[PDB]
Image (cartoon, rainbow over all chains, first blue to last red; front, top):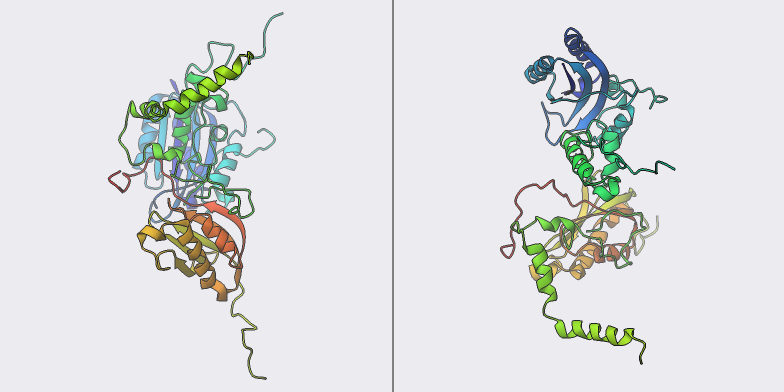
Length: 135
Length: 74
Length: 70
Length: 128
């Protein structure tokens, strides 16, 4: 099998309803003798054009070992979902060995790389736990 | 004596052979200005192979909506 | 036009040296022209080329200055 | 009540603060003071000061646009500005100098010219 990496997006209203998605995707990869090496949240990002009449949306990142056809299959699942509103999937990628790696990139998102339309607190109920003494 | 004080991706052959990766958008922030421009090799602290590889990852993250790309946003 | 600044209302400090968006600015390189593989270094050698009496006079000043024989 | 004063003792708003937005254009300069939410309160121009394209495009015409715009907002009780500028035109500091010299207090000057990631094909002047 292959090391993979997955990005996918949901609305801001769904940024604390994304762990319920990550449960199913995890269970697809663990079902396949694959393992989750990292799970991470990139938070709310600002959009050049409204999707379904709203200017912002929520990004998440997973980092895995999985068979490549699982991540073929999962890139297609995002692309067939209307709640999952855009993805990118990329071949031959792995997690960091670091704990809480993502907190420093959450910090970058809330500062210069959104337009901060929505509270930090709902988007942070996704992905990597912000253990600030590990990072 | 042996060994001497290396520079970023220096004194070795088997580092920065393959690309410097985009997922660390917090590290990528280091290599952009306050107008979302790329900084060249002499500023990232790296040589030609590694800067070409940085500039692909920097590009990637900004057009993925993960890294700053101007002083402005909407 | 004005860039961004730590300054207290700069308008009485005659800055122009960085104070552009396009006007002698770096983004003027693809704005309003063709691609030109040769031009942008050719046009340096050409611009310099005609003022040769004034060029040669500074060169001659420096050769006469440099020798400590006066 | 006495008979009223020869010049006003009072002024109907006192919002203190605003932004002078300048569009220093390739043929003109336009100055507008707006409240902090961007609703414009009054404006004035280079070109309306008796100048065509050929003279309205200068920092001296722009210098005068700033004075007529400082007068345009007098009743809204603003005195404190920050400044935002866009467009290729030279109406970008002589304007500010005469803006501050028409009884306002400037504290910041910032650019708001939009710059692209390559973008679309540019407009043409002198077939350039």
